[PDB]
Amino acid sequence: HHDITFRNIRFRYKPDSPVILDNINLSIKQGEVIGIVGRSGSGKSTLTKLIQRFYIPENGQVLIDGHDLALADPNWLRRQVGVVLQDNVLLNRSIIDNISLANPGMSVEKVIYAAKLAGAHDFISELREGYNTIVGEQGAGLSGGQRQRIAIARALVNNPKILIFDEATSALDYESEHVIMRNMHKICKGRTVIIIAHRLSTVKNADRIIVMEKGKIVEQGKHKELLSEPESLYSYLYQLQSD
């Protein structure tokens, strides 16, 4: 049973504009953890935008659970997917308000549980003002890696069946990165997960890696299989990022 299916997807952003996704066919099993890699501008984030029906393909179908998103209730869709956003923790509002920024009146218990999964609860709990701390530089002045764990907590708070990690746009501090990687199996448990990976190493242990180039899936498989394919783009990108 595939939680996410693309059939012959063709997409461009505007009537005259270039084709960004070209005959995308992909079927992701429930619970699979998938890494998506490739050069800048290869269409990685575009693929994830279509999962959320932020844009509509000119050809082909996106299905979640066998449900064509053309027909699906948009409120149902918003509830199926949690996205770990970059640069979206609002400095002028509380930690709890940043985590619950979808159903304001939702329980402190649900917030704390998401924060526990995300590896944020412990540091929030040692702040003078706790969850009521104003995130920003005058309030508690959290680090980028602390804000990122808050961003994970937000994505998780409504228990999404699909979790998408947007591509990292900043390097995280050691302790945050360590806590997140130590907690990934807990974060991902029971969910279908898509990680758009800036650094290939991030997704080495994903179930499958999808390699995009110029709007096409050119390669796909486990890390070791992709390295075994002669002259693979994956091997080339790995080589480029190597010490």
Image (cartoon, rainbow, N blue to C red):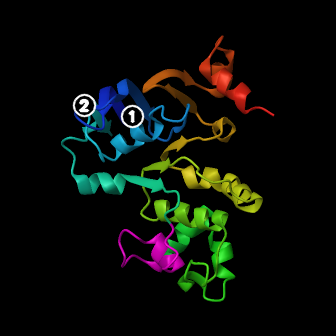
Q: Which mark is residue 16?
A: 2
- Kind of residue indicated by mark 2: Asp
Q: Report the residue marked by disc 1.
A: 2
Element under disc 1:
strand
- Report x, y in % for residue 40: 53, 35
Q: Nearer the viewer, residue 6 or 109?
A: 6
**Between residues 222 and 185, which one lies in front from this camera angle?**
222
Residue 31 screen position, x and y as percent: 49, 41
Residue at left offset 39%, top offset 33%: 1
> Residue 234 — which label?
none
Q: Amino acid at mark 1?
A: His
Residue visible at 58% across and 51% down in the picture: 169
- First reached walking from the N terminus: tag 2 or tag 1: 1
Q: Is residue 163 left or right of residue 59?
A: right
Structural distance between the alpha carbons of marks 2 and 1: 33 Å
Name which quarter of the figure residue 129 lies in: bottom right
**In this image, 227 relative to 110: left or right?**
right
Please provide percent x and percent y for residue 189: 55, 50
Report the residue that reaches farthest toward the bottom.
128
Instruction: State the predominant SS element of the stretch in magenta.
Output: loop
Asked whether, in this view, residue 137 is left or right of residue 104, the answer is: right
Magenta stretch encompasses residue 203: no
* Vertical arrangement, residue 86 with respect to residue 200, above or below: below
Callout 1: 10 Å neighbours few (<14), some, many (20+)?
some
Which residue occupies the extreme right position in the image?
A: 243
Could you tell me which secondary element the residue under label 2 belongs to? loop
Q: Residues within 10 Å of mark 2 (few under 14, many from 20)?
A: few
Q: Which quarter of the rendering shows the C terminus?
A: top right
Q: Look at the image and give the residue range highlighted in magenta.
A: 89-108
